[PDB]
Amino acid sequence: GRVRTKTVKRASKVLIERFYPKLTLDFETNKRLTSEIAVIQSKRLRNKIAGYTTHLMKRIQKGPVRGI
Amino acid sequence: IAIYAERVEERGLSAAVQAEALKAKLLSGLPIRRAAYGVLRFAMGAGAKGVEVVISGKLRAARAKSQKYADGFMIHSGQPTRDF
Amino acid sequence: STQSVQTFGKKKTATAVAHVKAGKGLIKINGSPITLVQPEILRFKVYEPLTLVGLDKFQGIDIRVKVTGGGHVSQVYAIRQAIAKGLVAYHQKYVDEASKNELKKIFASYDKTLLVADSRRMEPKKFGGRGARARFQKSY
Amino acid sequence: LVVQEQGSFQHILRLLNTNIDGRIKIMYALTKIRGVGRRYANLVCKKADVELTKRAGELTQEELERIVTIMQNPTNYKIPAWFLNRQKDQVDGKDYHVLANNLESKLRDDLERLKKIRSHRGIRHFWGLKVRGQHTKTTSRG
Amino acid sequence: IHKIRITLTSTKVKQLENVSANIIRNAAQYNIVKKGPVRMPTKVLKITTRKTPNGEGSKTWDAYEMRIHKRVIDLQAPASTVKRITQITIEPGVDVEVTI
Amino acid sequence: PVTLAKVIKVLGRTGSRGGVTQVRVEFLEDASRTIVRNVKGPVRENDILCLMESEREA
Amino acid sequence: PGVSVRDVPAQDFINAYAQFLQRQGKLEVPGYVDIVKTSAGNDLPPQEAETWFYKRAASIARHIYLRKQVGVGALNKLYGGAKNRGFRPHKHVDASGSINRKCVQALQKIGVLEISPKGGRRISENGQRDLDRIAAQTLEE
Amino acid sequence: DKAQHIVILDQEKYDRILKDVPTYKYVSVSVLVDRLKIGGSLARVALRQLEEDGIITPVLKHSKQAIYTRAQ
Amino acid sequence: LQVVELATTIPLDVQEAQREVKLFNKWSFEDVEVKDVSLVDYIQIRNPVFVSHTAGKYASKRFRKAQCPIVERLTNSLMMNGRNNGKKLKAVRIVKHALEIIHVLTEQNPIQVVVDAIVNSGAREDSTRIGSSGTVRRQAVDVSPLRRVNQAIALLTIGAREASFRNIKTIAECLAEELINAAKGSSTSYAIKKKDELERVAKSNR
Amino acid sequence: RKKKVYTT
RNA sequence: GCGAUAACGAACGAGACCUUAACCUACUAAAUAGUGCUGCUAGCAUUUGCUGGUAUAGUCACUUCUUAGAGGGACUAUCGAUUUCAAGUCGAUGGAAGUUUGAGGCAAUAACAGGUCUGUGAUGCCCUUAGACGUUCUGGGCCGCACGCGCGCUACACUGACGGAGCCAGCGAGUAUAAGCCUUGGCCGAGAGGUCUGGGAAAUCUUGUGAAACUCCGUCGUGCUGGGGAUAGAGCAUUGUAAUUGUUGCUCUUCAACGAGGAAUUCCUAGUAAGCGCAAGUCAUCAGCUUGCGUUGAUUACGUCCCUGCCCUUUGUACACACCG
Ligand SMILES: [Mg+2]
Ligand SMILES: [Mg+2]
Ligand SMILES: [Mg+2]
Ligand SMILES: [Mg+2]
Ligand SMILES: [Mg+2]
Ligand SMILES: [Mg+2]
Ligand SMILES: [Mg+2]
Ligand SMILES: [Mg+2]
Ligand SMILES: [Mg+2]
Ligand SMILES: [Mg+2]
Ligand SMILES: [Mg+2]
């Protein structure tokens, strides 16, 4: 299965809480941006964080989210 | 061939030196609690992120036992255990 | 030089390298005509990339493939893949893209393995059994 | 080509005091003859000029006698020595090929010739055990 | 002029590729024609033992490995130049063999 | 006298071992008489499996 | 177009070159052809006793034509097969050396092959001419 | 066992073949063995001769299967 | 229809194949139609193939098997009983001969006969067991369209295998007889006896 | 497991 | 994980991580990889073509395939459904890859009288220590056979046996003055094998490991038959100091049960199962064994707690050596 972990859920919502103006709805741009925002040790983990920041953006664009 | 001898820089971070010191203390009749905690505190004083001392065997009793003396933060699984 | 495109097709281990030069309708497998590809029952597997689009596309081109590795069927699939990809790459590079997109459309709509190599490979065998998933019979 | 015949076929043949089915191919009817295998019968038939495409009943008497002649005198018809059944015989040292009735006789004579000297192989033959050094843990249940 | 083959072997790839690049650079800025490096197929030294020292338990096996990486570089240069390149780039991990 | 019934909802796995599935069928003709029935093989929505007898629930 | 040996199916090419070599008749057949087995793994001699040697020479000639300086050890490996070991699993065993070497020596003195440099046996200047000829009189039907 | 298929062709059986084989929708080795009671080898030789005699047309040729039909 | 002259000569039959793709270049899919609505979506004949020897990738998702060609599913189910696993080329050769025998006998489209025997051979009601931990209990339940097809394919090849086992009649013509007979609904055939006994028990269980 | 007894 | 919440915020384990497999006509090069051209050269039609050979100087070019390092690529990406619209799940589309992308390595808190002192110049203690329980030499045994059980290999055939013919891999290993390594080719020999040379401390030679299933054409024709090759006789060689109680190989002959297997019971979800071989380990010799590797390659679910084992909650306890109480 593909249930994201807490190390990606919290790192993505920290990204959301800190760099919302610079983010976008494009995965490639979010992926490059988090490569210049965070020091991530592995590319695969980098892709998981950018994929969840994109998912969170699509959910904020669909309405207000609780807790962020 | 040429041999040079160099002193180990970080006494708290070298497990070989700490193990030799523990062996020389257990062989000197020192109590188990004082010997184990002397390296637990020496490692932390040197700045180690974590330390674990396990002593197993028989001590004045027919039945054998093992004692763990942990301290700080320690990781167990995966590559970082091979790295750190 | 001249009009030359070079490609390759792959199956499990078999790999066929195809050279497509400008010439007559010559289509060879390791220097041999396609009318005698073995095994016989699969000769239409390598006949498929030609008669499906129509053989007129091969008037102006000559194809020489070199297939090594794998087994008999894996080599048949490697040759037919190398042929289909070589023809597409030639149209894409030295002919109008209308022909290349028509060929890619018919090929993909008919069979996916014609242009994209199948990624399935053999699983390693693991101890405790005679196969990848099979295990030694247990007794109580 | 397909050919037909009437009255020439012999339904039951008798070779070396053994009844041989006449509708079997000649090579395997002689393979029915004890002491004559497929490898030996192909060669005695080629030395006797009996074409293998004939059934046993198809065969004539002249060829049948030429076959029993080959079977009884093999070395005289350029059959190689290494191809024979019983080579370097114990008593007279000559190359032989024993046949239907001679086979069990000389096999017997070999068993008694070994038991008289009371060798281990003869002992295990007497006991009915495996004699060639085989394990008897799981197979001596007959 | 002198046709020289240099064989580079090691267990770890980081230092092997560092030495290889440093030597190619010094054979580049010095106008010496070179052929290489040719990346030889890496050798996997595999040993598969049983985990259990006794013969009790589930039949589990360890499989240790020791990868050996090999590069060969061809140089056309005098021996003084080649020896001083070797001494500039001497490294404990990587072994070097020079053959004429 | 076979009757054909379109499925509109897969209810859930039933039976002791879970090898049979409850499904809600609707008749192709006379789009009424909706029935709950059990089916053995794997089922998606829009499977037209036919029924020998209709007047029985499951 | 120029027809070659590689342009004809093997089965009827070998049956045709074998037929030509038999009717032509100059190939010399060793005296043990009625006795021997092709391989130690085989259990019976070839069923077509009179013509098997000719067919084998035709196969050897075509195979060497399509390849380069194959030795007799390689031909033994090529024509060897699975041995019928009783209860143990099957294994590959080479064909007879004498049979292959005699076939190639007879064909070498009839003019189709010769000893190649750095080992093996190339196909002759006339070996190509007459194999391609047989191919031409092979594909008209 | 119980088979006892005929392997030798007499004249009565020969003419039985030439009188019965023409009235067949599909002839092969097994149909001939099953219903004409002849052996397999004799069936194979019968097919190879019946084609030369024109009674049977070979639709498809293979070693393990020989598919033939009536020529009428 | 024009014959295209190449330096490498191409046979006449394969040159007729640019107009149409036919199974083994002999049988056309154009005139084939399923005379039953319930198996149309699960017997795949819309995409023609030349040889039934195709690739896999159809054993991954749930209803992906319905997209595999029906003839390739038949030759896949044919290769059973251990000694035949992996002998796909042998299975394809036997099936290829079987279609010819089905064509020479009774004179119709052979792949129409295979489809008819498969639509006519899958039982529509099966009696599943509902035993509560040992006790004997049976309940009649329906069979999904996918299972009807793949039980038809299982029964035709099982019946052909057993009719050709230890019998002089060859497997290709045992499959041909089984397919034609099941196509015409005769109760003499296996997979019609099995289907009747199954649907009979299902009638005696509801 | 056994007691070695001598003869010579 | 969402969510509910006297809890909030954390750590280990899981996951991350590491190795391997699948993509890259995008970098970097490669005479220990391949190709196209070019010399020189052969055969067939003569159409200038098609197949070859040769080139450690043609003192050519290139990296598509081959190798391996630096990177890129997948994160459930996009679109539809269901869902607390949440975590997720199911379909398509794009994609090399959309089952944790496939497979493994590592792997928590305690613990077991689980297995090894027959791995240790690891060890405490007990026994022996000169007619040794030390070490060495000779011979026998570990193989011994009324029997019960387990892991497997051959088979019961025609989806097959022989006889010819076709004819494709990958993982690896390899020596020197040794004490004998991998062995091509030529020549003898029915075979096994013998003899003379050459290559390799190795992407170079063994090796294109021309492996087996597999494919084609023939013989056989449902027969314990040409399935099966045990049980044995005779003979010929190989390894070794030594083959007898037959090391193994080869020739002829001998032609057994077995005609698909009761009660029970094992393994298994995709290049998987099943066939099919090959290498490495032990190794002077011997592989029906393991560890890997590739060749051919499926049927059927993608669900449940019906059996079995384990886990959780409530509950009762006179148990805590914990119901073997
Ligand atoms: Mg982990
Ligand atoms: Mg397997
Ligand atoms: Mg004498
Ligand atoms: Mg072979
Ligand atoms: Mg062969
Ligand atoms: Mg995993
Ligand atoms: Mg120990
Ligand atoms: Mg076991
Ligand atoms: Mg065969
Ligand atoms: Mg063992
Ligand atoms: Mg309580």
Image (spheres, coloured by chain):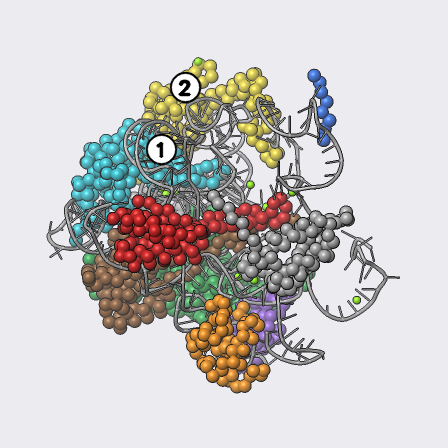
Residue C135's label in the rendered image is none
Residue K214 position within the rendered picture, expressed as x and y whole percent measured from the top left? 39, 49
Compared across the picture, whether A9 is left or right of J1 comes to: left
Chain I: colour as depicted:
green
Q: Count all numbered tags in the image, as a single digit.
A: 2
Disc 1 residue type (three-letter): Lys
- The red-tinted chain is E
Residue identified by numbered label 1 = G37
Chain G: colour as depicted:
cyan
Q: Is residue D41 visible?
A: yes
Quadrant of residue K309 in the image?
bottom right
Disc 2 residue type (three-letter): Asp
Q: Residue at x 27, y 34 (%)?
A: G103
Residue E25 position within the rendered picture, expressed as x and y whole percent measured from the top left? 33, 58
- The yellow-tinted chain is D
Q: Please state which of residues K195 and K70 is positioned toward the viewer in this rendering.
A: K70
Q: Secondary structure at mark 2?
A: loop
Compared across the picture, whether C69 is left or right of A54 comes to: left
Q: Give neighbour class at mark 2: few <14, some 14-19, many 20+ (Cα, 10 Å).
A: some
- The purple-tinted chain is F
Residue at mark 1: chain: G
Residue D95's label in the rendered image is 2
